[PDB]
Every structure is written in structure tokens, then in C-alpha cells.
Amino acid sequence: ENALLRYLLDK
Amino acid sequence: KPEPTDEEWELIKTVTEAHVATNAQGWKQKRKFLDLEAFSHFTKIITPAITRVVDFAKKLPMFCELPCEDQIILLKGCCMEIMSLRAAVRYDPESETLTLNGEMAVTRGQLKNGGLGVVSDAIFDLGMSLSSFNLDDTEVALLQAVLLMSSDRPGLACVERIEKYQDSFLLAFEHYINYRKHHVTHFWPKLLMKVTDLRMIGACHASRFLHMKCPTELFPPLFLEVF
Ligand SMILES: COc1nc(C(=O)NCC(=O)O)c(O)c2ccc(Oc3ccc4ccccc4c3)cc12
């Protein structure tokens, strides 16, 4: 999970 | 009283510009004064506020040197604390309002009945006491960096770098306070007590979230991913 957060962090 | 070193001025420069670049407006001239229906109106303005916090962390090189799962844990832990501090420093005693997203004045009662409960009181009382502190963009930025680099967040892997980063910020932020000579006694001890207050707010957002979980679909997806 945390897919949206992980997208915003990986630019 | 030791004043900042050269390397600490550079760290202050980085964190202050990161904060200013991700802090909405800069607000009292934009304010738009304002029960799942109040909860809906609040859920649907929160995703920009969470994203600004993400952009602030990404502008800190020490944060970028961490693995993405520690990065995720670190945002999830400090997101509401930073958003609460940013609203508390925008307390207007004449209107008794906080400013959300740089343009939305809210009252104690509006924000409480919007879903935060007694956490609304805690943020408002924090904004009241922060008036006589006269914090600038730098002192707020450093507060956000201290909260972000919390090595006690559950699940972290680089516990001992994160605690080193925080110790760096904590020292540069104390020397800045020495350099700045606020007309308040025992200022650095009182600031550390405010860090405790914001950490209390962070864990009480969490309790209020479990209480609110209303169908999960009605909660926006980033709001769900933070908690
Ligand atoms: C921290 O409180 C806020 N601050 C801002 C903001 O902009 N901060 C100023 C800045 O960053 O400059 C917001 O936009 C907020 C939007 C909605 C909000 O409602 C909530 C939030 C969390 C909840 C947890 C559990 C139950 C109910 C809840 C309701 C709070 C906001």
C-alpha cells in the first residue's frame, strides 16, 4: 500500500 | 550564548527556503471564512495541505538520502504536526481564527465540529501561546525539521541517521535562538515543550481518525494513506 504517497515521493 | 556556525547557517538557509516554498500564500488578505457535512468540507481541502508537507521534506537533502519506506514513515508521523503548527502560527486573536491552506479562516467550533474534536482546542491554545513567541519563517522551518526527523516513528530502519539529522537541526535551531535573543525567559526550554505539544497533537489526530472510521470511500485517498 501507500501507493499514492510513494508516487509523490519518487517524483 | 553560542550563535550559529557557518555550516548551520547553510542548513538554516536550506530548511527556511524549503518551508517558504511550500507554505501557502505568505494569507490574512486571502482568508475565506467558512456532522459528515462539515467533515466533507474539511476532507476535501486536506490533500493539498498534506502534499505541501511532502514537498517540504523533498527539499531537504538529508530526507532525500533516506530509503523510501523510511521516507513514508517519516511523513506519516509528522504530517498533522506540521500542518497544525502551520495553522497555529496563523492564529488571528481579533477574529479568533486559524488559517488553513493560506486562505480559509476557521473557528474553534467550526474545526471541532468538523471532526478533530478536542484536538481543535489543542491547536487553538497552541496558536494563542505562540503569539508572544514571535516565530519567524526560520524558527517554524526548524520546528518542522525536528518533528520530521523523529527516530521513534514505528517501523523505521535508519533510526540512527534520523536521530543524527535531528540533533543537527536541534543544535542549529538552538544557536539561531541564541543569535536571535527573544525577550522571553527560558526560550529554548519552552520551545522544546511546544515540540511535545505538537507530538501530542500528532497522536491525537490518529485517535480522532479511528473514531471517524463513516465509509472509508468518503475519506480522500491521501488522508487515508497518512493515517
Ligand atoms: C491540521 O489541521 C488542518 N490543517 C490544514 C492546513 O491547511 N494547515 C495549515 C497549513 O498547512 O498552512 C488543513 O487544510 C486541514 C484540512 C482538514 C482538516 O480536517 C481534519 C484533519 C484530520 C482529521 C483527523 C481525524 C478526524 C478528523 C480530521 C479532520 C484539518 C486541517
Image (cartoon, rainbow, N blue to C red):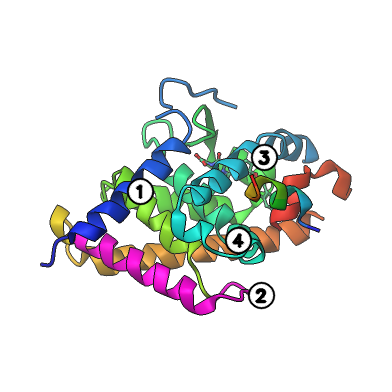
Q: Give the alpha-carbon distance from disc 2 to disc 3, as whole Å.
A: 24 Å
* Residue B76 image point, x, y percent: 63, 59
User: Alpha-carbon distance for marks 1 and 2?
Assistant: 27 Å
Residue B163 falls inside the magenta stretch: yes
Say whether residue A4 is left or right of residue B186: right
Circle 4: residue type: Gln
Residue at position x 53%, y 66% in the image: B200
B156 lies above or below B197: below
Q: Nearer the viewer, mark 2 or mark 3?
A: 2
Q: Which residues are magenta?
A: B152-175
Q: Which residue is mark 4?
A: B71
Question: Based on the displayed image, in which of its 4 quarters is residue B21 positioned?
Answer: top left
Q: Amino acid at mark 3?
A: Thr
Mark 4 residue crowding within 10 angstroms, few (<14) / some (14–19) / many (20+): many
Circle 3 or circle 4, nearest the eye: 4
* Residue indicated by mark 2: B155
**Callout 3: 10 Å neighbours few (<14), some, many (20+)?**
some
Task: Determine whether the beta carbon of the residue marked 2 sits less than 8 angstroms from the nearest atom of ligand 1.
Answer: no
Q: Which residue is mark 1?
A: B14
Vertical comparison of B32 with B191: above or below: above
B164 or B192: nearer the viewer: B164
Inter-mark Cα distance, 4 to 1:
18 Å
